[PDB]
Amino acid sequence: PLQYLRPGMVLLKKFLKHDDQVDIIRRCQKLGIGSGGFYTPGYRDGGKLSLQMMCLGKNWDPNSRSYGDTRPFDGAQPPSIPEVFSKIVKDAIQASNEFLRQKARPANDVEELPPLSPDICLVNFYTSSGKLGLHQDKDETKPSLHKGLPVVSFSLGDTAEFLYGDVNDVDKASKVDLESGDVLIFGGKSRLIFHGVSRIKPKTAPNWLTDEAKLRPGRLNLTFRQH
Ligand SMILES: [Mn+2]
């Protein structure tokens, strides 16, 4: 149910509840079509295919590769992060730290992820041909990175094949499947892993979610960070 991938990297299988997944899709469907909604980025670190994005909270701008209050190309301010999203993020960290507490026993230090008060949510939508190349989440402020403040990532819809490793070379990357409802956290010594999405597995989204949320083919990711 909870899986240790490497120091400070925990995968919470099927962590998102039924109604929360539906609620997350429905909120992103509505925010995604309004002001500050989804657009196709001209640039992503690592390259990309069949990817649209929108930010909640602070905006990450592709053209400038920095954080700000509004999207430069249309002046839109991003919607704020729903408080229910922030609640789930904090629960995921709490659950991870309890897992790391129980797995500690005693040839090594006790692991513990730092808390997160995310003010950045990157919402990525991949259609079935989607991909995102290996990259580091390296645009947050130096104190945020130096403290190892974690990245918390929600997965919904079709399964992603997720690559991660220490370098920009797939030959040295590990693979894990991120299925609908999974939450992945990387912080501490894993905060700067290279990572990406090599493939979306078509027709893997749960039928109940496709039906209740009217989800289009593909995968929705929400990636939370603290600037
Ligand atoms: Mn990333």
Image (cartoon, helix red, strand yellow):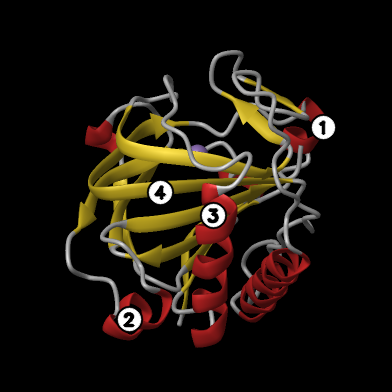
* Residue 38 screen position, x and y as percent: 49, 41
| Residue at 27%, 82% in the rendered image | 207
SS type, badge 1: helix
Q: Nearer the viewer, residue 158 or 165?
A: 158
Spatial separation of the CA atoms under disc 3 and disc 4: 9 Å
Task: Name the residue at the top extreme.
Answer: 64
SS type, badge 4: strand
Amino acid type, label 4: Phe
**In this figure, which residue is indicated by the disc labeled 1?**
143
**In this figure, which residue is indicated by the disc labeled 3?**
222
**In this figure, which residue is indicated by the disc labeled 4?**
125
Could you tell which of marks 1 and 3 lies nearer the N-terminus?
1
Q: Residues within 10 Å of mark 4 (few under 14, many from 20)?
A: many
**In this figure, which residue is indicated by the disc labeled 2?**
211
Label 1–label 3 contact, CB within 8 A: no
Task: Mark 3 and ligand 1: say if the CB distance to the nearest ligand atom is below 8 Å.
Answer: no
SS type, badge 2: helix
Spatial separation of the CA atoms under disc 4 and disc 2: 18 Å
Amino acid type, label 3: Leu
Could you tell which of marks 4 and 1 lies nearer the N-terminus?
4
Q: Is residue 123 visible?
A: yes
| Residue at 59%, 47% in the rendered image | 34
Query: Closer to the camera: disc 2 or disc 3?
Result: 2
Where 6 sits versus 99, above or below? above
Amino acid type, label 2: Asp
**In the rendered view, does 154 fall on the left or right side of 43?**
right
| Residue at 78%, 37% in the rendered image | 144
Label 4–label 1 contact, CB within 8 A: no
Spatial separation of the CA atoms under disc 4 and disc 1: 29 Å
